[PDB]
Amino acid sequence: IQNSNSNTLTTTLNMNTVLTSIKNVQINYTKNSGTVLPGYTPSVGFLGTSKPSLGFVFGSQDDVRYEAAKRGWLTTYQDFNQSFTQVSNKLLKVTANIDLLPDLKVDLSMDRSYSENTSEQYSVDPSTNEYKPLSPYTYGMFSISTVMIKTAFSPSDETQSAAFDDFRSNRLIIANRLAEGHYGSGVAIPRYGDANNPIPAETDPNYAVYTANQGYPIGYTKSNQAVLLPAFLAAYTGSDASSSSTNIFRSFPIPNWSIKYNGLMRYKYFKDKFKRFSLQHNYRASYTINQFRSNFDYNSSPKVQDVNTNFYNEIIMSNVNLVEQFSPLIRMDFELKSSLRVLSEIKKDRALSMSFDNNLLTEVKGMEYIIGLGYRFKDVIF
Amino acid sequence: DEVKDYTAENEKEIVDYLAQNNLTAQRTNSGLYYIITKEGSHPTLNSNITVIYKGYFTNGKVFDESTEGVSYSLRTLIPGWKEGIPLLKSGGEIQLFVPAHLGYGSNGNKTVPGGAVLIFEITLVSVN
Amino acid sequence: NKYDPATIGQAGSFLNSNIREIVTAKSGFNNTNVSEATDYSVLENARK
């Protein structure tokens, strides 16, 4: 038996009818869902059914597994290989409009996407008819609007990058914060260079790992995803790693702006050789996790450290992408009374992708300068 | 930050557990309590061990167990095991009273709340 | 079997820590008759 929802909510929320500059607040919220329950023994009637629950027939997504097993209409086979599956998708597209100045048009946009897939095997205990989930796991997608304009204009090339130096330095701060979260300040934080965790001999397999991060806490090296993901985000968003969040996901989308300024006509440009003059500026940045998954290594066993002595992470991901785009950074579109058209614009984009497979940061930088000249000589004699 | 201290309350809970149950346990410098029920005929940091351990909270509910032998590296485990397992040889059994800072920490994980005292009944069957 | 990556060179493994390095890949085997393209193969910048 299967299930699905297609929840949709569209609102215009006209702020009209200091803060009165806000004009429209358009909000779109889409929430899809779905459930697949295999091993369901009962049949259906001529006109339909309500046997598992009336809500499930109308896409409730409320749990029915345990009630269905209790009522004895799940399969009694103890080696059932079909998986109970649940999916959930969310999309938020808040859009705003501001009128700070009479001739200044500002558009704001907020985005947040979140996908979630759950899967598990199951069996029903022959006694007490209790539902037994087996090896449940999770994978999903995340995306959210962010702002990293603070590091957008710091020079970064093959020879120097201030933001990357911040990324290097933030690792120890984030590791210390995580260690204080794990070792709750009641004891001295164990470290790779202290007496209790000495650097081993040259023959030991962990000599190099211990030497590489001497002063880091035991479970939080420079290679731990939980350490360097918040370090990466804080470094490239221009945040302070001492207080920036160490969470993988973000709740509040940071708005991105679209600025249109058709206002220089009213200063002196009526008869100042200009017929029109417009300035435009668009900024758009997103933080994306293409695929995160639950970790079977993150369990209740006493084994808590991986081969690199890092603590196991509940949610693992291969990559995280930070994308920023000035489209355009500035667009000077103007015309002179001699009909000299100029359309000059600058574009800028950054495509930071940090890979946790190889712990390498791949940075794609772009620059585009466009100049469009339009002139019309009048009455030229051949 | 939300740093929480559990050393004192874990210590008092452990000593209360050793009070209600007629058990005497030796205490380490790190706050770990252990009891040697029997001794066999010592694992190091780089040593593979096989255990038949059983882990439960102070109220008796089991959070992790291995009725059959499971092999571990003894350097990837929680610090409480790293301090307790080297105390005996193959065939011996130990009763651990790992506090939170030697166990899963102030945050814990799923099925183990943060700042929880762990109790382990570990049998070391081999140090292969 | 004894090729388990988790137990590389612990007590009785068939692999040493040299197995992790491309240059010393051949020396990473404890067993004797090992060939560079039969028992194993190496890639230096393998793409996922």
Image: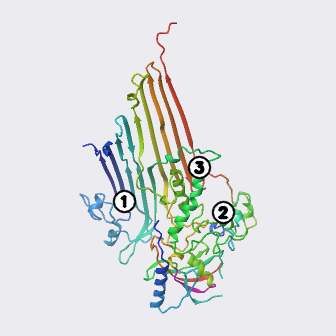
The residue that mark 3 highlights is A162
Which kind of residue does numbered mark 2 sit on?
Ala
Output the chain of dot 2: A
SS for callout 3:
helix
* Circle 2 residues within 10 Å: few <14, some 14–19, many ≥20: some
Q: Earlier in the sequence, mark 1 or mark 2?
A: 1
Distance, label 1 to label 3, CA atoms, is 48 Å
Instruction: Tell me if residue B69 comes above or below residue A253 in the rendering.
Output: below
SS for callout 2:
helix
Span highlighted in magenta in the image: B88-98
- Let me know if marks 1 and 2 both belong to one chain: yes
Q: Earlier in the sequence, mark 2 or mark 3?
A: 3
Q: For the point 51% across and 49% down, which residue is it? A: A322
Residue B117 left/right relative to A24: right
The residue that mark 2 highlights is A212
Q: Does any portion of residue B56 appear in the rendered image?
A: no
Instruction: Tell me if residue A365 comes above or below residue A138 in the rendering.
Output: above
The residue that mark 1 highlights is A35
Residue B33, position as x, y percentages in the image? 54, 84
Residue A218, position as x, y percentages in the image? 59, 69
